[PDB]
Amino acid sequence: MQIFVKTLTGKTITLEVEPSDTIENVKAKIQDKEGIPPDQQRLIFAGKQLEDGRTLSDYNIQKESTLHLVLRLRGG
Image (tube, rainbow, N blue to C red; front, side, top):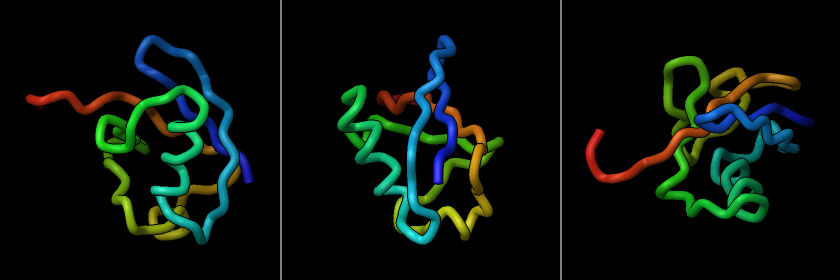
């Protein structure tokens, strides 16, 4: 099933995913596509960061849901 990932500035990256697979599986597509490594990738649904080793069903992320892609540098 597909979701939507939005970058900082506001490019939308349409992205396909499997709901009982993990956030790591989401990140490996983003990492193929754009090329940000998964430590530097930070995916925000709403105002929670999604944990790595959990599924999309855990968070309750579904078809045609918007995730926001911002980065991880050093400070925060």
